[PDB]
Amino acid sequence: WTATSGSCKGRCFELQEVGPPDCRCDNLCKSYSSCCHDFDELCLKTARGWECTKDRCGEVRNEENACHCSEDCLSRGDCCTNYQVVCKGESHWVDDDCEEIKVPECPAGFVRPPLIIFSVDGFRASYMKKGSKVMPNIEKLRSCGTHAPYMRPVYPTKTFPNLYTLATGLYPESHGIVGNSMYDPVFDASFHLRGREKFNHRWWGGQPLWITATKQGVRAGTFFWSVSIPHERRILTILQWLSLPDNERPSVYAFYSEQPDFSGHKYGPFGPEMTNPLREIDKTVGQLMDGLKQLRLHRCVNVIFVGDHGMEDVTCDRTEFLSNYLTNVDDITLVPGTLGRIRAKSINNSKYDPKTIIAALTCKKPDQHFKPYMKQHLPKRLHYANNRRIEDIHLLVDRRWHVARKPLDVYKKCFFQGDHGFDNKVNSMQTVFVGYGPTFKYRTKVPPFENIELYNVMCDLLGLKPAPNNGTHGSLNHLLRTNTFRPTMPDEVSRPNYPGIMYLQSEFDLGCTCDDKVENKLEELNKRLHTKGSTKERHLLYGRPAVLYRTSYDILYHTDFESGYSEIFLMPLWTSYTISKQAEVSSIPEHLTNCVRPDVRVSPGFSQNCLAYKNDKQMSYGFLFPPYLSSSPEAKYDAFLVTNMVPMYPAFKRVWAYFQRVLVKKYASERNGVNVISGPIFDYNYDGLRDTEDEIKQYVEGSSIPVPTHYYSIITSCLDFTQPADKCDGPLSVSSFILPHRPDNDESCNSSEDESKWVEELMKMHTARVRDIEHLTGLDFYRKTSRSYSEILTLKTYLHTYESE
Ligand SMILES: *[C@@H]1O[C@H](CO)[C@@H](O[C@@H]2O[C@H](CO)[C@@H](O[C@@H]3O[C@H](CO[C@H]4O[C@H](CO)[C@@H](O)[C@H](O[C@H]5O[C@H](CO)[C@@H](O)[C@H](O)[C@@H]5O[C@H]5O[C@H](CO)[C@@H](O)[C@H](O)[C@@H]5O)[C@@H]4O)[C@@H](O)[C@H](O[C@H]4O[C@H](CO)[C@@H](O)[C@H](O)[C@@H]4O[C@H]4O[C@H](CO)[C@@H](O)[C@H](O)[C@@H]4O)[C@@H]3O)[C@H](O)[C@H]2NC(C)=O)[C@H](O)[C@H]1NC(C)=O
Ligand SMILES: Cn1c(-c2cnc(OC3CCOCC3)c(C3CC3)c2)n[nH]c1=O
Ligand SMILES: [Ca+2]
Ligand SMILES: [Cl-]
Ligand code: NA
Ligand code: NA
Ligand SMILES: [Zn+2]
């Protein structure tokens, strides 16, 4: 109950919300049916429209008008945004040449440049080029400021997950807004777009920018606008707030546009009906910039123009129905559309089985347009698993398609021609970023980057210390003229041992055998120097990775590769090797097919054993440095060391062998040499973070050898591919992957065919950032390069997406 009989007089768009049942006059009151009786009359004035005309100039202040063209309007802060243009011979902001903003040029009393966040729903990245003729204000922001060709949203590429990621710097799994629709089993409660539950604070985790600012004594504009308040009124309200006295005036403001998303759903992303919504958004930008210019704030404010996600062509006829696959369709609940989430209809049904649901959904039709996953098997780059609100069973839906439970759900719910929500790598889901203002660079293009990074930069823009988040602070310093954040490399926690020869062959009883008892002063000083690290500068190009947690591990040198070997996990944490463009691929000699050799630098007690693999009928083994790329028949023996061995399911060995035999040489040829770092990952609790020993759920049978959940590789070369990887003088180029270590290849529907038809497609799907691998392993890479640390942070956040242009 609200006693809606108080008044909004003098209170219109008040900045602190009042506690029921006193009536409200803030920009959100409509959404709560809590505005005072007189809110529309006082606060939502529309008389005479939104623009000064010739004959309104100098007029007598009529307070009924939506905006004013009288003489006192400038000092009142409530002129129509085109006042000075109509009545003072001034030019529109878009018609002025842009001039570099070297320093903030602000009115007296401003302690920092204000930040205005202008967010647009469904603004697909290619609108910047394709709609440029009809968006002159936006094009001026873009070309005069700092811009990215596109900005990558988070998954799912839905509105609320992405806006809240923008606000928090957190993945949806961490902030808790994991879709536009959700069930939380602990609350036993549901979140929906329509309705009241979404207002309850328990849905909304992390610390959004407005709370960060408030806690640190930076005043924030109430960010959110009830939908019926028109755009013109939102802009005028922001401009009025910017006229408050210094002690009351916010330093950060937000504008949100429901367009072009609203129309994009109805007409598709490039429907001829889409020109008008784009023109209208540009006009709103024009009104803000003209308004700032009137207030002499146009060279003082930092403006961010940012989208939440793009929009793809999707129609009712491109719907797959679970009723075409499942006999038991009534025993499941589906969250439907551009992603699928499945759980049991009733928790009292003990006959429901996710195993059989997944199987009935796997590779059942030749051109099936969704793929089912247990959430912990989704590509790690999605970071979409560690939340009780994310159902165990997930469907990744092909772009341009929908999934529904039953055909009745679609024709009793063709309306729409656009939608979004798909894999955040998809080109049509990419969105926009432009930063314009004193703190951004002038006429600068920056590479594509992920929206999780922006919270840190908005904090930087406001002099705020960011709450802990998933951005990599410093990776976007290259957007900024000043206020950069100067991070330090994390300190190494564990230093390595460098073991020499300490064990005799006969101390090992690992049940391993090798055909290698075959016999020199020249070449014996040689093998010794290699084992002391003589070739190390060739194979470890960027320093050894730092171990950022407490553990016991050894560095092992070899002719062709270097590794950091964990005495706790009984395998390398990392193995580093360089493969030049000239390198040759050889095969494993026949006599060496099942060769495993004891490593006399590492005790039997800290070694794997071959008997455990023999006894484990499910588990086999592979090598991290591939024997195929050995530099000489003699160096090849190093590759069969028990300290280079890792457990591998036979089904995964198909993947791994093709990577090592075919793909590594292919990249070396294409990139003029590559450096490769590979290693195991353990993430049994699917939280994206390195597991401790006591979190490991699976061991090679009868042993203490832990089974990795994933294998990674980081493949670095010179960005200037005219220089070989091992002799590179400038910026680097990287691609990485985190392959799930699975006992079957059910994920790849064509896996009964030759690896040349399916493995590279699997690797692409599991593309990753170096930063993702750092979280998962507790390692820090690129410790010693000649590049600036900010530049290295950017490289560590790079994702190679394999989408076309
Ligand atoms: C992306 O960035 C984020 C932010 O940095 C990273 O997430 C952080 O990771 C930390 C490590 O996992 C984690 O630290 C834990 O904090 C626990 C206290 O948590 C509360 O307080 C914080 C701070 O205000 C708050 O943010 C949290 O909010 C979460 O929970 C509510 C709902 O419950 C949500 O509204 C909110 O969205 C958020 O949920 C997310 O995080 C939780 C995990 O905390 C997930 O479960 C959710 O699914 C969701 O993803 C909390 O309100 C603290 O209690 C933990 O301490 C335990 O472990 C330590 C090790 O130091 C041990 O010493 C302690 O004994 C303790 O163990 C005890 O509790 C155990 C569990 O019950 C029990 O098993 C033991 O036996 C002990 O009794 C821990 O330190 C931090 O909370 C989150 N922060 C956020 C915002 O999510 C994230 O990792 C990054 N992702 C990647 C890929 O890098
Ligand atoms: C969807 N929505 C909104 C709305 C607008 N902006 C938002 O976040 C932005 C605030 C500024 O920083 C950039 C993020 C949010 C987040 C989701 C809570 C919601 N308002 N009205 C409406 O329908
Ligand atoms: Ca983990
Ligand atoms: Cl959703
Ligand atoms: Na075996
Ligand atoms: Na298969
Ligand atoms: Zn939408």
Image (tube, grey):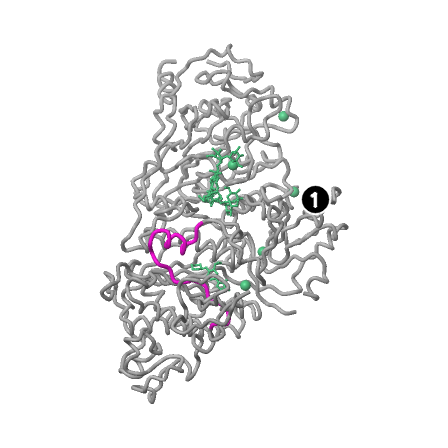
Eyeballing the image, is 638 above or below 75?
A: above
**Place of residue 325 in the rendered image (x, y in percent of width and height, measured from the top left):** 73, 52
Q: Is mark 1 within 8 Å of ligand 6?
A: no
Inspect the magenta stretch and tell me whether residue 213 lies in it: yes
Q: Amino acid at mark 1?
A: Ala
Which quadrant of the figure shows ligand 5? top right
Q: Residue at x 28, y 61 (%)?
A: 438
Q: Is residue 509 left or right of residue 404?
A: left
- Identify residue for label 1: 359
Q: Residue at x 44, y 55 (%)?
A: 166
Q: Residue at x 57, y 61 (%)?
A: 196
Eyeballing the image, is 537 above or below 297?
A: above
**Residues in magenta?**
207-229
Inspect the magenta stretch and tell me whether residue 109 lies in it: no
Eyeballing the image, is 676 above or below 604?
A: below
Q: Is residue 305 visible?
A: no
